[PDB]
Image (cartoon, coloured by chain):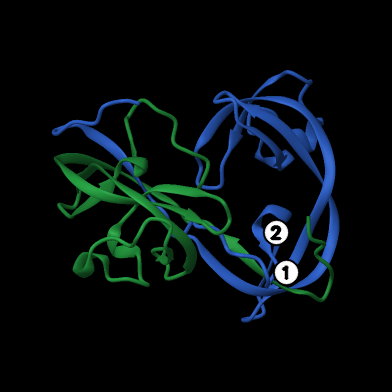
Chain colours: A blue, B green
């Protein structure tokens, strides 16, 4: 909605999404937090360790409705409110070079589905 | 909805979105295509040169309703249908090292707005 004009300083976004084939080595249970970001977007797969205003692994979850600061993997910080938790899964995957990482369900695609235009 | 199991080969997505401060050097007019992807998602800012099933810069736009193949910047190809065109703007921006690039409005953020969790 905001007008962008000659001479203005702005921030530009540059995507570099990568995709890799991998093998599922394990499926485990994981506690996730549900938070409403100040922008109105709602996340149900926030890691407890990504709340940086309260050390939730040491002190337990925030109170429901509590204002929290959430870190995104690139270090950007966001205001949100904590609204509860759920238990879901993490998927341990192995790459072609033998390296491994644990992934959330949202970041996994079967070999049959279209990969997103996010790249 | 699909079940992911131990021993399965899957594809995993890894974001690496970067953000940079830059200066707007020019605002120009640009013809964009409007396409409906087979997945039901609708784009209004597709570049004519990103239709790869018809060379639209040489032969003009596809017919309305025509099946097209669309390339995404990472080379992934998608089926879609062409549904018309519009004229919008491109923003020529300059980075701190003096390099420049033309950007779509969707990829530009003012210094006041929150940057997205896409990173």
Q: Is residue A81 above or below residue B47?
A: above
Image x and y of residue B80, in percent: 48, 61
Task: Relative to B69, say whether B103 is above or below.
Answer: above
Q: Is residue A21 left or right of residue B104?
A: right
Say which element carries label 2. Answer: strand
* Residue B92 appears in the picture as rendered: no
Q: Residues within 10 Å of mark 1 (few under 14, many from 20)?
A: many
From this view, report whether residue B79 is shown above or below residue A53.
below
Q: SS of the residue at dot 1?
A: strand
Question: To which quarter of the image does residue A15 belong?
Answer: bottom left
Give the x, y percent position of residue B22.
23, 42
Marks 1 & 2 on one chain: yes
Give the letter of the chain under mark 1.
Answer: A
Q: CA distance from mark 1 to mark 2?
A: 7 Å
Q: Quadrant of the N terminus of chain A?
A: top left
Q: Nearer the viewer, residue B18 or A49?
A: B18
Q: Is residue A75 visible?
A: yes
Left or right: residue B68 versus residue A78 is left
Looking at the image, tell me whether mark 1 or mark 2 is earlier in sequence order: 1
Q: Which residue is mark 1?
A: A93
Query: Where's residue B56, x and y in %?
Result: 26, 65
User: Contact, CB < 8 Å: mark 1 with mark 2?
Assistant: yes
Which is more toward the observer, B19 or A62? Answer: B19
Residue at left offset 84%, top offset 68%: B5
Residue at horizontal 32 percent and vertical 29 percent from the top: B111
> Does residue B92 appear to the left or right of A75 in the view shown?
left
Please, which chain is the residue tagged with disc 2 on? A
Q: Is residue A3 left or right of residue B70?
A: left
Residue located 48% across and 56% down the image: B16
Q: Which residue is mark 2?
A: A103
Could you tell me residue B45's position as x and y percent? 35, 48
């Amino acid at each position: 909605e905001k007008v962008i004009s000659v001479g203005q300083t702005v921030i530009t976004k540059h995507r570099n999404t990568r995709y890799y084939s991998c093998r599922v080595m394990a499926v485990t249970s994981q506690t996730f937090y549900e938070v409403m970001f100040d922008d109105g977007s709602f996340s149900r797969d926030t890691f407890p360790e990504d709340i940086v205003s309260r050390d939730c692994l040491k002190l337990g979850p925030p109170a429901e409705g509590e204002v929290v600061q959430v870190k995104w993997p690139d270090g950007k910080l966001y205001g949100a409110k904590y609204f509860g938790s759920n238990i879901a899964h993490m998927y341990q995957v192995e790459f072609e070079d033998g390296s491994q990482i644990a992934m959330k369900r949202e970041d996994i695609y079967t070999l049959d589905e279209e990969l997103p235009k996010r790249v």
